Amino acid sequence: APVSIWSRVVQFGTGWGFWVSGHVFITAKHVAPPKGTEIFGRKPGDFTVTSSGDFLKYYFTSAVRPDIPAMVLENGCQEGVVASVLVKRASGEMLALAVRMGSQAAIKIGSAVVHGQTGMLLTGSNAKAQDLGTIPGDAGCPYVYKKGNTWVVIGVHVAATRSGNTVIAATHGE
């Protein structure tokens, strides 16, 4: 009966994004298509767009996906929480990566300080040797966890370190 969580993750621009609800879609700003692109067969004027750092939210005034009930969105989680990154690949593969969430920490470079949260993959020290870490292009995939019985989404993937153990999620509530 209930909608799979994976079905909320869809391809978008040069990465992916997540239906929080029937009206709300989120992604990483740096993978999105240009301002004024028709998306999901919608014109500009059918939606409003808000962004904090590399977090990007579309709100469609008329629901795009009535089938999908609203999920609690949060601005990160308590540190130490084990969340999952729901990574889809263009091959079709779906990889849920366990990640221990670190501290809310904000850096690309100086004078362009974007905000998010780090975590370490629980996939081990040699995640990229195993084809079990992320790649750029997984950007936009969601980070989620289960608080009690309730599911909640906390951010979207932006990047990983060279040796892929540390990952970075963009956050906010909007």
Image (cartoon, rainbow, N blue to C red):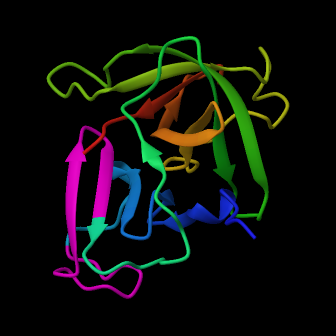
- Find residue 42 and report its horizontal and vertical position in percent: 32, 85
User: Which residue lies most toward the front here?
Assistant: 149
Magenta span has 92? no
Q: Quadrant of residue 68?
A: bottom right
Residue positioned 82% across, 28% down in the render: 129
Give the vertical position of 165 relative to 37 (above or below).
Answer: above
- Find residue 152 and report its horizontal and vertical position in percent: 52, 41
Residue positioned 30% across, 55% down in the render: 57
Task: State the extent of the magenta-drawn residues as a range.
Answer: 36-58
Q: How many marks?
A: 0
Quadrant for the N terminus in the image = bottom right
- Find residue 20 and report its horizontal and vertical position in percent: 46, 57
Residue nearest the viewer, comparing 166 with 46: 46
User: Which residue lies most toward the right here?
Assistant: 130
Residue nearest the viewer, comparing 16 with 151: 151
Give the vertical position of 99 relative to 4 (above or below).
Answer: above
Lateral position of residue 130 relative to residue 100, left or right: right
